[PDB]
Image (cartoon, rainbow, N blue to C red):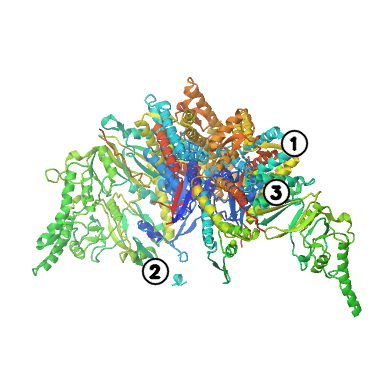
């Protein structure tokens, strides 16, 4: 990954490749992006790493949700399938411990 | 400061994403205006007029945009409308779908040229499959032509009066058909004029065996009803006029002034006598007719009409079998138009209209439209234009292709089956643009109001069978129907043009990765 | 020759290096030396007329309208409302001469002006300015030794 | 004037704000060759397009009024070398 | 002190500014080079859209204020004028040459030495190209023309359809072939009328064996098809006669006015009667025709087309054997029209093309002409097809006139870089560095080709340079001179075998023009910009 | 792009991404280096920078020039940061760091333009820097003899090399001897605050002196001060932190009396408190009294009556320096003024230096401090003299820490370039180009020296390359002879840590600049 030079409203200079820091310094305005940022910050507070994973996975999930909604599915059905798959993934994850 | 201060330039993935999104927005504007269950839209012109239609071309024409990709899509709509006259909404939707499909791969590390090559291969295979699944048409069977026109007009507001509109369009097209010097033509634009008079009822609309103009006799004493007129058409005025060279006179004798005026009158009389020599009954001119000329014609019992437009005069010549002559002294017997079976100047509403409506074997016609208002009549005229364009497309090319998304699914399945033997990097865009054709059944189902996913899956499973190329979606009941039973068929030429135009629009918009703006015309 | 450099990019995007670089001037190379020598020459030529018994006074008026008729070079330069940086350097030189010795506050300015005037035509012939400074230092050492040699003592 | 622009391509219909150049706004500048020719403002006092067309044509201001080709033909205008036949 | 009313920038400041302007102009078009290049969309303030890939068009449409950038813009325009191909490559090469020359100058290398080195390097590169890197097209046959056209149309809106468009271009060029004095076969491209019309796909574009006019018959009464046409080309208007400014009609006897007015049109009547009595069928005139003459032609059952372009009329007359007649006057002082002035064509029709009509003069005799009708999705696409088609026609003309072609895909650039790097060591001291930098700068083209394809530019160019160095060092491995880039797979490939050629004139002219432009901008060391 | 009815970031946010952003960063670094190029070498020139207030700063120091610039480019500020870092860690090389970093970036710009992955360039820089630092540590010359005269000579040579680029280069031997003498008297921590630097206008550069003691300006004398003697031949110094004047006993103290006798007693008590403090000071035997707090006029007159010297409001730094030089101790209470808390100096004297009165405490035999009294004809003259002396002092201190020296004039960097090129000629080839670019970039300093001197850079570069290749380590640029010479034998010496830190900082800055692919600037808040 490549570091990013981010200048906040106070002209302070941040150069980093930490996703949480980039989101914090960026002045996000869209409420949905704000919600994703809050999820990323919750991940940072709870664990301390994996924020960029949170952003990437959320973006991929929402893109594929848009695809599913366009191909004729309903929002509730997509949500139910996502929850079922998340439960299945949480079930599978302990079996992958090396 | 190398370039101008107002010059704006951007490049990269941002330009591609913006172009694809603009095309998608253009598609989404008119997505809900496809199929027999389409809903009309009201367009407010900058001039104050109201356009009320569901035809794609008019809606896209009455919209001003800034993004150049949107302008390209508007031009594609105009090209599809001008070339074949039908399938205008379908091509925009198809282009948007292919552009979204291409963006899918563009987000990955695939170069646009690979996508373009796959698109062109898919277009060639699409053309081949469409030609393969076509069926012939016997144009001598009026029933088949009427059914084709009906299937063309079921999606418009004129579908309420379907048989009347189909008969009008078919009769007008067959009547305007002409052949000369071994060259066939239809030429709906010039002849076969559609004239709309608000009021009355649409059921009273009809196609005339001749023409009709908004003109009245120049002098009341002339006959307003002639049984079997002989019609003479002219370009030149029937009035004394100046010459090109400066021709100042010089009068010294007393009687020269009176003599000059007498020669003016005598010239008018000579012109009128040359006209009368052919013994006509109606005289039509594209320019003025002098009052003395009116008197001299009236002494010979001749009806004279003046200030007729050149296009209307040509239409009259085609209808009554005459020839426009600009020099009355060079008027031959062949120039006199015999073949007009009736001429009648009658009153409709508060305006006088001239009818020549009993012609034997006319090569021009006027479609008299009567309706609730000007907007309704404009929509009816657009629908009739679509019907006549479809009729002439069938007459020129007698092939036929199943409609209602059956052809889309059949071609998609054929291309998908062909894609199993590629084993290349470009097979993915090939398959993904093959499946992009499923948008037409998808939007048909969506407009019908039924479940998209279940019906689309059922249709795909049906098309996986061997003899199911004609299985499509019923656009008004949301059920799978064999289109050889429903009867919805549409010309092969329209399908070919739509697919070519959509694929080439996608190709054109996929070759752009930089936008520069703000520079002046500089010539 | 001023207002920095006008490129604004190599590609088209904005290119800002220094705050308010559009309102900042800059002088480069020999032109800066020429301007400095010209300013110092002007100051020295102004101050040289007040040298010696036949020198003429300068009438200085401050911002309040007060009048100060004087011959003291250090006072004249102190009350002068210069803006050029080299002129301020000349004023500081005169004040330093006043502080350390108290006399000859005009001779220093005239001598510096003449030195820079000669250095101007030396630079026009392609000599590096540091070489000129080194030669001036060597000659100053020689002159100081000669002054010590020819000095005389008083009771 | 948008409609008239289609009829008369040679004209250069344009707009301008009053601020970019108080009585100016509350209470049609024709230029030909760089000098003012027509000097009519508040033309609403003296509506649809052909009315304005007649209003301007009555004073010999609007130029006198063509077939719509496929799209266009022009390619270039330079030393063509002509279509020399032989020798 | 100087008191000049303006801005004066001198030395390294102005040198860097000039190099910055050249580099910006280069970067404007660097992304439109090679088959993996992409088109650009240009929007005016009016809102017009011009999708294009041609470098000359892009640089002509842009608004440029820096003179050092205007120099490269007119350089591209000149390269387009005298060659027609390689307008982007010449700009890129010139900008890179200027960049490396400035880099050398900043190391206290005098600009005169750099200019001398650049001149020597350019001369030696041209000599090496002419002596080692040219393939005679005599033994290749017709395949060389097709391959050259396909290579020219790569990186264009018609690149994929090259298999068909190259055949169209070659046939069109060979149709207009003629030989002048000295037995030189000259190919007058730009005599092929390019007609654009949206509608069917690209593959429905038609090559007309004859000529195509973007004009229709004057009157609807005339027939729209003549089988055995007798074309009459005229250069005067057929209207009512009007006496000249020096002649004025003054009538003293009223009995003569009617005769005057009668003759006023009877003169034109007699002229048309002669024209039609000689046996003519199709009449084309640059001037206008009024309704009376149109009715004369309608009655005669002939064709009459007005407002025909002068160049189109000249092409039709030369193709069909007709002679332009600005007037009907013989050396006997009479008013006559001979049948020897009539051109003949096997057919003249009026076809409908997407709700519009154009006149097709088909299969003219005494000479063969050609025209191309381009069908596209919209106007912008047709414009791009026309530009690419003109580029292909120019390339084919260059290949046919001078029968030498060079391998494409950066093979020439890599070979020249290696050869000049070797040769620089044998000439001068500082100009040796100048020639070395010229050789290095020549490598920008393969680098840009690799970069635009998102391939490993450094490794690929290193492999190409290794191949060419082995070819030059080893006499027996001399067959590797044709090794060029294959951006489809991102690996070196023998481009001569693959069929990637281009005229030698393109490379030679681009090199000379880039060297001259670089020298011109390098000679500047001071700028005075007076305030208007 | 599209209107996007709800925008993602704040309106006015600027974003740049891709190769153009990185090459723009490299160009900005080039501009920053150009802003300071001509201040390098014995022929370097000073720069005059004027701030908004109109004050002029004249300097030959790269760090000072870069700080005075209002650099706002995010990439360019890294050069200023590394220059300040070099100034903090070493004190010299503030121009070399910026030149080397910008030259690294310029060398790798062509490879950046052709789509090379920045991580490869970063790895190449890391490897080259590690190898260069190892080579410097290997070939640096050290003498393990602990000889006083040899160590003194090494210190003097290092100081002369550090000073031979400033306006005091003509008297560089004099100032280097002064600096070396000043540094060795520091005890163990080499604290910079123990070397006072006084600037007095008027006088020649050679008139500046190093006081083996402490000197400070006279501090606002009161009435009766001129009656005190101004020279003592063995004075005892009473360093104090005490306010010696009539004042309220405490801020919140209040006196409540109901008798005139108690009123008179209170007045006499205040007078007796002051006189008791003064008498306790006087009976200690001290003759010079220095206090951080003000000394009142009554105390001044009392001391004058006893023929004693007083000086109130002395700065805290000057009191600490006086205590370190003399050996006493600063006292806040005068109750126990034993002989162990009183400083002693051989001679105290108040003299005039160019229109200012200064107090001199000379003759201290165990003094751990010094005081430079810099004479000059202008304020900026003295400021630049102080900056040059600071550079020399930092070099001498670092040399005290470790006496490892290398030859200057680009000789060390020519040797490093030769070694790096030889190493790069033996690797597979992708890293070969980058390490060769690093080695070629290591040639900027001798080229800049030649350019500033006005020579022909290319000829000197070729001669240095030929001599280093054919054997020879310390061959650099000879400015006076317009040729090359063995700079080690020419006593152009530098501490090895200077070049080590310069290379480390330049490489880190280059890697940081290269590692960035996108710059985002949020709109400014509270613009007003
Ligand atoms: N009754 C129907 N049931 C299902 N599909 C239909 C029916 N009538 C028309 N269609 C389909 O709708 C499409 C025409 O949609 P329309 O709104 O006319 O778009 P356009 O105006 O662009 O032609 C045709 O492809 C045809 O196959
Ligand atoms: N099929 C191909 N394979 C490799 N290189 C090619 C191919 N076709 C063209 N090229 C090269 O791409 C380069 C760029 O050509 P282009 O930029 O399109 O022409 P112009 O410079 O006239 O715009 C040419 O030098 C040519 O040698
Ligand atoms: N006598 C000398 N001869 C040649 N070069 C010298 C001499 N003295 C110093 N240098 C060079 O000058 C450079 C230092 O210049 P200076 O501006 O004083 O400090 P900085 O290292 O901060 O640039 C060193 O690289 C050194 O090689
Ligand atoms: Mg992590
Ligand atoms: Mg339809
Ligand atoms: Mg005196
Ligand atoms: Mg080309
Ligand atoms: Mg130094």
Marks 1 and 3 sit apart, C-alpha to C-alpha, by 24 Å
Q: Is residue F506 visible from the viewing direction of this image?
A: yes
* Residue C42 position in % (x across, y down): 51, 58
Say whether disc 1 or disc 3 marks the residue closer to the N-terminus. Answer: 3
SS under mark 3: helix
> Looking at the picture, do discs 3 and 2 lie on one chain?
no
| Quadrant housing the C terminus of chain E | bottom left
Q: For the point 66% across and 48% down, which residue is it?
A: F388
**In the drawing, what numbered circle is on residue D41?**
2
**Residue B377 picture location, percent across and down:** 42, 58
Residue E3 percent coordinates (x, y): 44, 56
Say the numbered circle drawn on residue E389. none
Tell me the subunit letter for badge 3: A
Q: Please give the label number shown on residue A96.
A: 1
User: Is F306 situated above or below B466?
Assistant: below
**Residue A97: which quarter of the image?**
top right
Residue furthest to the front: C155
Dot 3 corresponds to which residue?
A40
In this view, the residue in front, F262 or E246, is F262
Query: Element at badge 1?
Result: helix
Query: How far is the residue under mark 3 from the one under mark 2?
Result: 62 Å
């Amino acid at each position: 990954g490549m570091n990013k030079m981010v200048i906040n409203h106070l002209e302070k200079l941040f150069v980093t490749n930490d996703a949480a820091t980039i989101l914090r310094e960026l002045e996000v305005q869209h409420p949905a992006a704000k919600m994703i940022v809050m999820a990323s910050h919750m991940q940072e507070q709870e664990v301390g790493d994996g924020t960029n994973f949170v952003l990437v996975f959320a973006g991929a999930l929402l893109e594929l949700a848009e695809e599913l909604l366009r191909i004729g599915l309903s929002v509730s059905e997509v949500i139910e399938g996502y929850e079922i798959a998340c439960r299945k993934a949480h079930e599978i994850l302990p079996n992958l411990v090396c | 400061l190398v370039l101008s201060q107002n010059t704006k330039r951007e490049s990269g993935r941002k330009v591609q994403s913006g172009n694809i999104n603009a095309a998608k927005t253009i598609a989404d504007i008119i997505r809900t205006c496809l199929g027999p269950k389409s809903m009309m839209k009201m367009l407010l012109d900058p001039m104050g007029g109201i356009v009320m239609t569901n035809d794609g071309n008019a809606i896209l024409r009455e919209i001003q945009v800034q993004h150049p990709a949107a302008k390209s899509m508007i031009e594609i709509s105009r090209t599809q409308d001008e070339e074949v006259g039908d399938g205008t909404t379908s091509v925009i939707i198809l282009a948007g779908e292919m552009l979204s499909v291409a963006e899918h791969f563009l987000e990955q590390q695939m170069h646009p040229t690979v996508v373009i090559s796959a698109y062109r291969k898919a277009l060639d295979d699409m053309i081949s499959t469409l030609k393969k699944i076509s069926i012939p048409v016997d144009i001598s069977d009026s029933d088949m032509m009427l059914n084709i026109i009906n299937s063309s007009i079921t999606t418009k507001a004129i579908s309420r009066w379907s048989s009347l509109a189909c008969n009008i369009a078919l009769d007008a097209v067959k009547m305007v058909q002409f052949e000369e010097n071994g060259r066939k033509e239809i030429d709906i634009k010039k002849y076969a004029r559609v004239e709309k008079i608000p009021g009355g009822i649409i059921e009273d609309s009809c196609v005339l065996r001749g023409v009709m103009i908004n003109k009245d006799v120049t002098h009341p004493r002339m006959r307003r009803y002639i049984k079997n007129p002989r019609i003479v058409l002219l370009d030149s005025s029937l009035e004394y006029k100046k010459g090109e060279s400066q021709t100042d006179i010089e009068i010294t004798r007393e009687e020269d002034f009176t003599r000059i005026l007498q020669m003016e009158e005598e010239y008018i009389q000579q012109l009128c006598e040359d006209i009368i020599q052919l013994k006509p009954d109606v005289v039509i001119t594209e320019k003025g007719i002098s009052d003395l000329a009116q008197h001299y014609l009236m002494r010979a019992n001749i009806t004279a009409i003046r200030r007729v437009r050149k296009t209307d005069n040509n239409r009259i010549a085609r209808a009554c079998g005459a020839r426009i002559v600009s020099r009355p002294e060079e008027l031959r017997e062949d120039d006199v138009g015999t073949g007009a079976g009736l001429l009648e100047i009658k009153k409709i509403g508060d305006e006088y209209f001239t009818f020549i409506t009993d012609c034997k074997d006319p090569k021009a016609c006027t479609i008299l439209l009567r309706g609730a208002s000007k907007e309704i009549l404009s929509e009816v005229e657009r629908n009739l234009q679509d019907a006549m364009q479809v009729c002439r497309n069938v007459l020129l090319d007698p092939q036929l292709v199943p409609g209602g998304g059956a052809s889309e699914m059949a071609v998609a399945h054929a291309l998908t089956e062909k894609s199993k033997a590629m084993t290349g990097v470009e097979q993915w865009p090939y398959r993904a643009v093959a499946q992009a054709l499923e948008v037409i059944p998808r939007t048909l189902i969506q407009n019908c109001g039924a479940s998209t996913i279940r019906l689309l899956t059922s249709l795909r499973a049906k098309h996986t069978q061997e003899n199911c190329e004609t299985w499509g979606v019923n656009g008004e009941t949301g059920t799978l129907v064999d289109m050889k039973e429903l009867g919805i068929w549409e010309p092969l030429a329209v399908k070919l043009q739509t697919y070519k135009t959509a694929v080439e629009t996608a190709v054109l918009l996929l070759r752009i990765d930089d936008i520069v703006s703000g520079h002046k015309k500089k010539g | 020759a001023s207002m920095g450099t006008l490129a604004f990019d190599e590609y088209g995007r904005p290119f800002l290096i220094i705050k308010d670089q559009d309102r900042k001037s800059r002088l480069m190379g020999l032109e800066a030396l020429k301007s400095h020598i010209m300013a110092a020459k002007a100051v020295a030529n102004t101050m040289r007329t007040s040298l010696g018994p036949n020198g003429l006074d300068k009438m200085m008026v401050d911002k309040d309208g007060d009048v100060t008729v004087t011959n003291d070079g250090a006072t004249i330069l102190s009350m002068m409302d210069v803006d050029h940086q080299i002129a301020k350097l000349m004023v500081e030189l005169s004040k330093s001469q006043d502080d350390e010795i108290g006399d000859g506050t005009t001779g220093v300015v005239v001598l510096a002006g003449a030195l820079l005037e000669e250095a101007e035509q030396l630079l026009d012939r392609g000599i590096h300015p540091i070489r000129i400074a080194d030669g001036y230092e060597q000659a100053a050492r020689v002159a100081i030794e000669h002054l010590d040699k020819i000095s005389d003592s008083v009771l | 004037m948008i409609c008239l622009a289609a009829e008369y391509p040679a004209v250069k219909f344009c707009k301008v704000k009053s601020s970019v150049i108080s009585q100016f706004t509350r209470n049609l500048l024709i230029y030909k060759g760089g000098e003012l020719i027509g000097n009519f403002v508040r033309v609403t006092d003296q509506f649809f397009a052909v009315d304005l067309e007649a209003f301007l044509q009555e004073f010999g201001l609007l130029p006198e009024k063509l077939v719509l080709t496929s799209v266009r033909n022009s390619a270039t205008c330079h030393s063509e070398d002509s279509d020399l036949e032989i020798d | 002190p100087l008191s000049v009313f303006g801005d004066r920038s001198t030395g390294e400041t102005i040198r860097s500014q000039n190099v910055m302007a050249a580099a910006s102009i280069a970067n404007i078009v660097k992304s439109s080079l090679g088959p993996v290049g992409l088109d650009k969309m240009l929007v005016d303030d009016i809102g017009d859209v011009t999708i294009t890939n041609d470098g000359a068009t892009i640089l002509k449409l842009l608004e440029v204020e820096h003179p050092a950038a205007k120099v490269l813009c007119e350089l591209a325009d000149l390269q387009d004028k005298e060659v027609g191909d390689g307008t982007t490559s010449v700009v890129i090469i010139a900008a890179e040459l200027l960049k490396n020359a400035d880099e050398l100058v900043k190391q206290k290398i005098h600009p005169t030495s750099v200019i001398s080195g650049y001149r020597l390097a350019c001369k030696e590169a041209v000599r090496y190209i002419n002596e080692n890197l040219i393939v005679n097209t005599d033994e290749l046959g017709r395949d060389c023309l097709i391959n050259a056209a396909k290579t020219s149309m790569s990186s264009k809106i018609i690149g994929i359809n090259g298999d068909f468009f190259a055949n169209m271009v070659v046939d069109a060029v060979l149709a207009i072939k003629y030989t002048d004095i000295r037995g030189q076969p000259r190919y007058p491209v730009n005599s092929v009328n390019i007609l654009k019309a949206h509608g069917r796909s690209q593959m429905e574009s038609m090559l007309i064996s004859g000529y195509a006019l973007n004009c229709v018959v004057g009157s609807q009464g005339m027939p729209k098809r003549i089988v055995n046409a007798k074309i009459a080309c005229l250069d005067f208007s057929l209207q009512k006669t009007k006496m000249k400014l020096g002649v004025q009609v003054v009538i003293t006897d009223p009995e003569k006015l009617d005769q005057i007015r009668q003759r006023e049109s009877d003169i034109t009547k007699e002229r048309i009667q002669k024209i039609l009595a000689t046996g003519a069928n199709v009449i084309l005139t640059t001037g206008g025709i009024d309704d009376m003459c149109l009715k004369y032609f309608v009655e005669a059952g002939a064709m009459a087309v007005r407002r025909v372009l002068k160049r189109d009329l000249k092409r039709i007359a030369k193709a069909s054997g007709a002679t332009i007649l600005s007037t009907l006057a013989n050396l006997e002082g009479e008013e006559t029209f001979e049948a020897a002035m009539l051109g003949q064509a096997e057919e003249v029709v009026q076809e409908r093309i997407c709700d519009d009509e154009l006149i097709l003069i088909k299969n003219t005799k005494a000479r063969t002409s050609a025209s191309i009708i381009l069908r596209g999705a919209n106007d912008f696409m047709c414009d791009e097809m026309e530009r690419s088609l003109h580029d292909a026609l120019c390339v084919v003309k260059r290949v046919l006139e001078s029968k030498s072609v060079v391998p494409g895909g950066g093979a020439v650039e890599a070979a020249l870089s290696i050869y000049l790097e070797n040769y620089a060591t044998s000439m001068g001291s500082r100009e040796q560095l100048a020639i070395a930098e010229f050789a290095r700068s020549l490598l920008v083209i393969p680098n840009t080709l690799a970069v635009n394809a998102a391939q490993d530019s450094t490794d690929l160019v290193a492999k190409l340079r290794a191949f060419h160095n082995e070819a030059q060092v080893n006499p027996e491995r001399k067959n590797l001179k044709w090794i060029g880039l294959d951006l489809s797979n991102g690996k070196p490939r023998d481009n001569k075998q693959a069929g990637v050629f281009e005229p030698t004139i393109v490379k030679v002219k681009s090199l000379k023009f880039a060297t001259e432009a670089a020298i011109t901008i390098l000679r500047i060391d001071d700028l005075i910009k007076l305030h208007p | 792009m599209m209107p996007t009815p709800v925008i993602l970031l704040k309106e006015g946010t600027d974003s740049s991404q891709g190769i153009p952003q990185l090459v723009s960063n490299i160009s900005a670094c080039q501009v920053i280096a150009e802003a300071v190029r001509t201040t390098l070498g014995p022929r370097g020139m000073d720069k005059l920078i004027v701030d908004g207030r109109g004050k002029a700063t004249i300097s030959n120091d790269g760090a000072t020039i870069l700080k005075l610039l209002d650099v706002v480019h995010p990439a360019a500020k890294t050069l200023v940061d590394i220059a300040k870092s070099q100034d903090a860690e070493v004190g010299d090389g503030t121009t070399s760091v910026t030149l080397l970093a910008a030259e690294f970036l310029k060398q790798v710009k062509p490879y950046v333009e052709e789509g090379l992955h920045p991580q490869i360039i970063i790895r190449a820089f890391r490897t080259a820097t590690q190898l260069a630092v190892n080579k410097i540590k290997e070939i640096a010359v050290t003498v393990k003899k602990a000889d006083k005269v040899e160590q003194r000579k090494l210190l003097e040579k290092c100081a002369m090399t550090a000073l031979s680029s400033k306006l005091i280069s003509q008297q560089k031997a004099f100032f280097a001897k002064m600096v070396v003498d000043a540094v060795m008297m520091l005890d163990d921590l080499l604290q910079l605050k123990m070397i006072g630097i006084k600037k007095v206008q008027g006088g020649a550069l050679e008139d500046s002196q190093l006081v083996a003691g402490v000197a400070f300006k006279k501090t606002f004398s009161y009435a009766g001060f001129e009656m005190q003697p101004k020279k003592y031949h063995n004075p005892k110094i009473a360093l104090l932190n005490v306010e010696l004047e009539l004042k309220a006993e405490k801020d919140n103290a209040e006196i409540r009396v109901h008798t005139v006798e108690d009123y008179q007693a209170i007045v006499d008590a205040e007078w007796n408190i002051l006189y008791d403090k003064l008498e306790k000071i006087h009976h200690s035997g001290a003759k010079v009294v220095l206090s951080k707090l003000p000394i009142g006029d009554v105390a001044t007159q009392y001391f004058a009556d006893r023929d004693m010297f007083c000086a109130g409001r002395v700065p805290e730094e000057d009191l600490k320096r006086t205590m370190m030089a003399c050996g006493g101790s600063i006292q806040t209470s005068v109750n126990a003024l034993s002989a162990d808390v009183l400083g002693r100096c051989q001679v105290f004297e108040e003299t005039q230096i160019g229109g200012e009165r200064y107090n001199f405490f000379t003759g201290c035999p165990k003094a751990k401090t010094c005081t430079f009294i810099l004479r000059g004809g202008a304020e900026q003259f003295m400021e630049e003299t102080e900056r040059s002396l600071h550079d020399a002092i930092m070099i001498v201190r670092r040399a005290i820490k470790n006496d490892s020296v290398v030859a200057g004039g680009g000789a060390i960097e020519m040797e490093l370039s030769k070694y790096l090129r030889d190493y790069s000629r033996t690797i597979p080839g992708k890293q070969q180009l980058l390490i060769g670019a690093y080695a070629k970039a290591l040639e900027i300093i001798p080229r800049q020296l030649c350019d500033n001197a006005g020579f022909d850079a290319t000829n000197i570069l070729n001669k240095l390359r030929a001599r280093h290749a054919q054997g020879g380590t310390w061959y650099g640029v000879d400015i006076n002879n317009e040729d090359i010479a063995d700079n080690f034998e020419a006593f152009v010496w530098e501490p090895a840590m200077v070049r080590i830190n310069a290379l480390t900082a330049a490489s880190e800055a280059a890697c940081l600049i290269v590692s960035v692919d996108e710059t985002i600037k949020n709109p400014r808040s509270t613009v007003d």
